[PDB]
Image 1 (tube, rainbow over the protein chains, first blue to last red):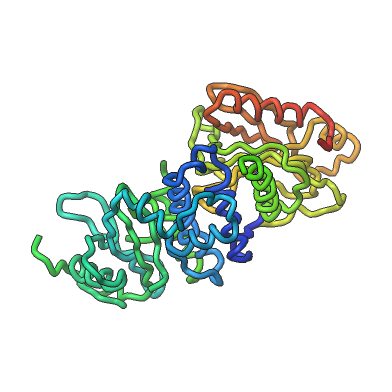
Image 2 (image 1 turned 60 degrees about the vertical axis):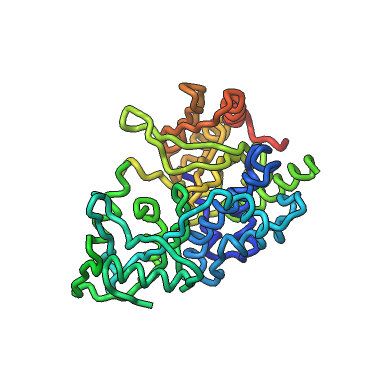
Length: 221
Length: 174
């Protein structure tokens, strides 16, 4: 109710981290601070909020992966990291003991910006971006266009992604604006309006990235 | 280091909130996991605000100061007018960037205002609080009825008795 401003869209990366610290890391019961596995999840949690909101509010900020963002929180606020091992080293041995399935897809948009490209499965009556499993030693952007060739059939061709972990699957959906809306897409393998989607989700994977996708919409205009 | 941490917590919280409400003076209370529920459809609605709760003191202050501008019954009623509100409530969100807020001004200053200078920028009905159904019931200045949750029943009364002191008492400096 009280009118508080929007300082994320105008402040330093040093400050943006500080905020996110208050938000996700620092105000927590000691249990979630005296255990490595726990704070590595709150870093996971704040890196997503950074990539899905902070980066989208302030464009002068760089695109940060959980790899580097943690390195940054460790430097600006070194009071939270008590232990001797490095985060990079820890979030591999400990957090990624929770072995994830990286799924590469994309949120497809039109040149006029009014519609999104989501498909429905054969068995599933649920709408989502072209989502499929990864491989060995291949760039996240090359697995993205290849999976959009298998499920729709149109390669588009980097840092503009939307990371999120959902029940042991690392979804890193990239953002591509500018694909023909008239073009006919068909499955190359054997076996909606944005206005219409905003009103529908408000009534209480794409069901979670509504607000970051609305931030991609509010910005480009 | 276990105590050097809580003093850094008061520092970080404060100047993080100072960037949100620029009129803080003294951070009075902070709890680590709150959730807001709203009343209207004769039942509670889980609002999209979840994170650390904080109750602070506002520098009111430079009289004639603007309550500035940030960017149907479901939307809140933003306070517009003069900066006259004595204390603040804030849930530092984790859901989306916009945080939660409640202006908490005593009835002691309201009755002092409403009678002496009847130049009310916004209609203000004095605030009241209670402990009901594992939630802290808060009746706001713009009639809005909210409810804040915390797991501990100790914490629920803690924030209640403070909110209650703030409104039933005169502007302080602790």
